[PDB]
Amino acid sequence: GPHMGAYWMSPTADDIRAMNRMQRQRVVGFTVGRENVGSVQFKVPVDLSNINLDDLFGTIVILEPRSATVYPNAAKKPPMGKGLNVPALISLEHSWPRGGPTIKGRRLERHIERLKSIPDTTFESYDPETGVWAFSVEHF
Amino acid sequence: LRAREAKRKATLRMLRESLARVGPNVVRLRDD
Amino acid sequence: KIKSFAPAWLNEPAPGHKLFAPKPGPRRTIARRGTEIFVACGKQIRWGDLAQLKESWESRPSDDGAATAGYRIIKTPVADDIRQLVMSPNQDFLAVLTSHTVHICILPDSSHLHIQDTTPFKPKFWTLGPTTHVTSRSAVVSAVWHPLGVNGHALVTVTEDAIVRVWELSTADRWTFDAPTLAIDLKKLADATYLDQDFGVSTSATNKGFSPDAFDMEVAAACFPTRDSGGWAPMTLWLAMTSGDVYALCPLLPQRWTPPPTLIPSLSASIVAKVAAAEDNPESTPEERLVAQQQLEWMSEIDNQEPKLVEEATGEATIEVYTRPSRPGLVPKLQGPFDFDLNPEDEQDDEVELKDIYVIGEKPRNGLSLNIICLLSTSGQVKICLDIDGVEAQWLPPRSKNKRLFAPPPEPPSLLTFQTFDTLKPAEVTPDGWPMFSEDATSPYSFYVTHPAGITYISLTPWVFRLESELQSDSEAGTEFRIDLLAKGQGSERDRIFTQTRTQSPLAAATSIDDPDLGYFILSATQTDPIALFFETP
């Protein structure tokens, strides 16, 4: 039963609220995360001018143990390139084999093979000493 | 009152250890 | 006289041959009730009685099929080739699966097989989860009827993305087909801490996210134990992932359920005994006492409950109906991944990767007082595991419980690997093959393995009987001596009954039939021809 921490974003919601109409259309290095779960780092400037910062956690970006979802409702997902439907760097903690952290040998390297083969993802890294799976997506 | 459970537990423990002595009972097939 | 693998009354130009004559996944395209069989061929189901079709070819002189006795066509509303047919317990409902969709066929009166029948022939088909089991969502992997479902009308479906859905069907209420009574996301449950957390599924959650469980909890198959099982077995859903892992859910019940007369009293004794052992033992951990507590709480909902009495849909007799206990919770703990003790080392990828699971439930204290979990790999490897510890009812803790730092880590659940053997030669192994288990009609401890390469018969008798006798042994001594001989015994027997040569055509999952008139035989089929191999005639 992995502990689900609190959501967070960078820049903070306060910082984004303080941005003018120009700046909020091109928030650089926008990141949404949840402690002891993972994070989504968008790899381009994003347009947050039509996104409620008070209804972002759990509504648009859902971070659960071993699970990252952006725009969970397919019907209300913006076109590719608009909103948060852009390339991103996702990191998921606790992404070890279901057998547990104490899995080595062929079973562990088999797991890394399976991570690389997950469709619509580009494998970045997996570290057994932390259990963090990092990978890139082009859209959601 | 019910010592049969200890007997079951011991019996199955013995099956395990017995299967361990023989080693993995693996029967694979060859082409010919 | 071409060498065929079926009797003359199932080969062309016999009328019985019409049942058979005209993509990765399982092919359970044959189902049966008595001597009747249902054969999926594309988007239609071919219905026929083997008894009449036999007689027609024996008493021969020298298009819905209404002109042919003992043969009828069943057109279906499916939009893709049928993959699986699953007969219900009382054999009145038939589950019809494509890769993604599920239809329930209300099986028609058998009188429609006679030529004399002039009345209109339009078997009712019900769509199951129109917005749930769809091509735009996760594929359906297993459909199994709940052993304890009222009127045998409770169905469990499982998808690749490990969502378990219980449907409690009533033809008098369309809504029962539209939505499930219970929906469990195993991926949420696996990582949950408390029994009251959210394990449900959102109708709005249509866009897939990203997770290692996309492969690690990709479901290959699920089953309930063979019925006539005792203890917790008939409330235990077993699952096998393509990753090689095995899971169990217990107790999984629909909102309402029907136990055989002996189930509840046997469980009560089992629960009472477990509470006693937990309390009497001073070395009992607070985690061990909680399981006993939760089970006692579950049972208390049943003791203080008066069972309702309702008719049998296909019957002439009333039976007790209970409601599911609400405490400790509706969703049991997900148990697993099970550790395979004495597992073979250096298993290959196609040996670890699972494609089917078949569980023979413990029998009340005729057979073995232990669950037997059988696992089928892509390679056709079969693994026979024994549930030494005994899977039982478990739930996650309540939020009332305070986490203790000096508490030991929960050791993973375990199965004992008793035996592992190939059923295919290396040359017969296909990289994406989907071999299937099938139950034997005459004994739960025998079963079949079907694969495009061929069909194999397997039996765990008399070995399971020898183990049970030792478990019930009246002898003061000699246990370790006698067990050693049993472990040295070859155990299960296996024999190939059929081999397909130079034909990559997949075979319909073997269907065992034991009729007093037609005899005892296996039924399978190629894309075009039948396979009926007999073992005992009258």
Image (spheres, rainbow, N blue to C red):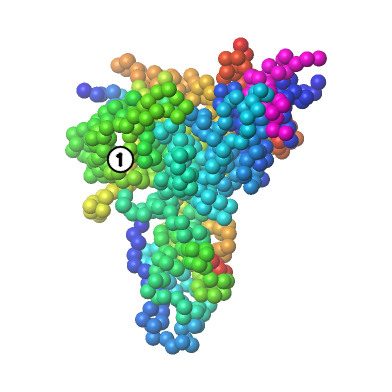
Q: Quadrant of the N terminus of chain C?
A: top right
Q: Quadrant of the C terminus of chain C?
A: top right
Q: Secondary structure at mark 1?
A: loop
Q: Residue C66: within the magenta? A: yes
The answer to whether A139 appears left or right of C295 in the picture is: right
Q: Position of residue C149 (x, y in %)?
A: 42, 34
Query: Among all residues in the image, which is located at the extreme top?
Result: C538
Callout 1: chain: C
User: Is residue C390 visible to the viewer in this orientation of the structure?
Assistant: no
The answer to whether C200 appears left or right of C285 in the picture is: right
Q: Residue C241: within the magenta? A: no
Instruction: Give me the residue at 33% from left, 34% from top.
Output: C322
State whether residue A98 is above or below residue C345: below
The answer to whether C405 appears left or right of C347 in the picture is: left
Q: Residue A70 or C137: which is nearer the viewer? A: C137
Q: Residue A128 or C87: which is nearer the viewer? A: C87
The residue singled out by tag 1 in the image is: C325
Q: Which residues are magenta?
A: C48-71
Residue C176 image-quadrant placement: top left
Residue C251 image-quadrant placement: top left
Instruction: Give me the residue at 26% from left, 53% from top.
Output: C399
Q: Position of residue C33 (x, y in %)?
A: 56, 26
Instruction: Give me the residue at 47% from left, 78% from top.
Output: A50
Instruction: Give me the residue at 38% from left, 78% from top.
Output: A13
Q: Residue C461 or C204: which is nearer the viewer? A: C204
User: Is residue A73 visible to the viewer in this orientation of the structure?
Assistant: yes
How many other residues sit within 10 Å of disc 1, few (<14), some (14-19) or many (≥20)? Answer: some
